Amino acid sequence: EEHANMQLQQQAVLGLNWMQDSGEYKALAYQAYNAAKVAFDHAKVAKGKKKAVVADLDETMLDNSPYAGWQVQNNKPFDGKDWTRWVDARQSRAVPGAVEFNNYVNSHNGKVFYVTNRKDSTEKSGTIDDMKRLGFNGVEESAFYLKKDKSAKAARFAEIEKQGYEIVLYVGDNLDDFGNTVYGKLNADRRAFVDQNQGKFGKTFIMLPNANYGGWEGGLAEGYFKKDTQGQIKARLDAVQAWDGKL
Amino acid sequence: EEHANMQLQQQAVLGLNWMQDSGEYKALAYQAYNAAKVAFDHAKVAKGKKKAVVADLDETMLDNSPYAGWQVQNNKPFDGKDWTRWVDARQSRAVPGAVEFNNYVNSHNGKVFYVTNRKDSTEKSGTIDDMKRLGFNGVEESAFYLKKDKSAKAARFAEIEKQGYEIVLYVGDNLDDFGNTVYGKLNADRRAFVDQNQGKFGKTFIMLPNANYGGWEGGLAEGYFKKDTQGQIKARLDAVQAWDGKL
Ligand SMILES: Nc1ncnc2c1ncn2[C@@H]1O[C@H](COP(O)(O)=S)[C@@H](O)[C@H]1O
Ligand SMILES: Nc1ncnc2c1ncn2[C@@H]1O[C@H](COP(O)(O)=S)[C@@H](O)[C@H]1O
Ligand SMILES: [Mg+2]
Ligand SMILES: [Mg+2]
Image (cartoon, rainbow over the protein chains, first blue to last red):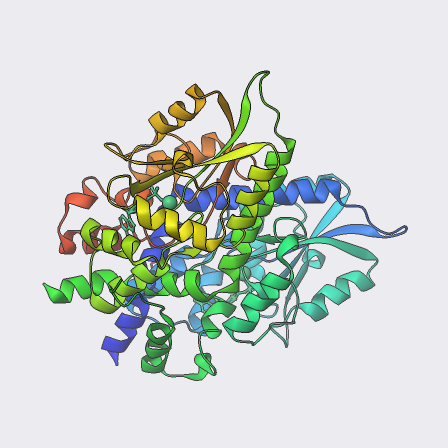
């Protein structure tokens, strides 16, 4: 139903305006990357290890908001086939502060590795071209751990460690950018993970804001991503906590 | 038109889900307050001055999301008269990390002053009662600079300084929580302010995320807040930056 597709995508509009237009969003990005530099400079690693920073790409270092805008204008639910075309379009932007932080790490005895769910086989060329264009240093192919067979990221983190790196901090917009312990879990478990790691945020786990999509969306209801459009609308509305209007 | 009211409020749904349900939102709140403590501990003031922290309340220390939920469920655009009832309902929650930070400052040779656009004359009693209940220390009436005749906050900051305080950092979810220089301005000017102060974020200007309302909403279009519902819908949709779907 076109009506349902429209309602689902209209629900993203205000958060998209915030991400695309607000100074507040930029300020949060700068806050994150300012904190990240402090953490990187403070970090010490075990003898014999090289210093690594793990960074997510989508909505962490790369800004894909025009794809979300296209979804709104065309009443299009997320589809990986459209995403691949977006990546190939080579119109990604940089999240504020990301290039400077990336290049600083890479010139100060660290290496940023991009652990990203852009697809290795179909989305790599556009990703690398955009990052070169946007000014990122250190974007040789071996810096990337793009998605092959699994969206969960912990195994890729382990690959980096096997290459003699100690990961000093992680940057992301999704809790699944910090490990696998709440991957595929609902939001109660995800909030619990955050509470259990309260002191790490802004230190070793650096957060960027994303009000548009992520593991928190699937976290709204059991089986969310397999529901039809009407089901996803209902899951979102049922998750709302509302004042009853009384004293 | 009820139809227009519904569309306007439906546009807030996904960002509301993110703020209310996601672990990611909590992580951003903890990140902000963790950074704020570091900044407070580092701060030194001029000889003879007392250390002050200025904090916003709404969507910075207090969580009003159930009011937004009520707007969604009842297709209600923002109305100050409903807001006053919400405040009187005494159902505000605390933003994660806020109480701990507040109480830490107040027990470590600082004082938090609440510079807030809750109304001094009609919204003070509920605010103070909720803050006591939520565990905030230092909520005697004189700690509050609630709204009297002006929403812009700089004059209240100056009042605090006149009382012999040096403000070591500001906490807020709206750029207008940091001064008046982009008060009432559109988002291009607001983004420019942020760029001009890039290094202050996470240091002396501490940001909390708010994808639901604020100066950035008015910043979407000249005269936004005076437009009717249809006009505000159009302003939001016209602000969207969309991929054209081509390579
Ligand atoms: N609106 C969306 N809903 C669900 N998935 C999305 C959406 N937008 C992009 N994606 C997919 O999620 C991936 C995010 O990768 P990540 O590494 O930031 S977890 C993208 O590369 C894309 O594959
Ligand atoms: N959805 C909204 N749109 C516009 N104004 C709002 C909305 N929700 C609350 N407000 C008003 O804005 C004030 C915010 O105060 P502040 O100090 O965080 S700038 C609230 O006390 C209330 O007076
Ligand atoms: Mg991401
Ligand atoms: Mg506020």
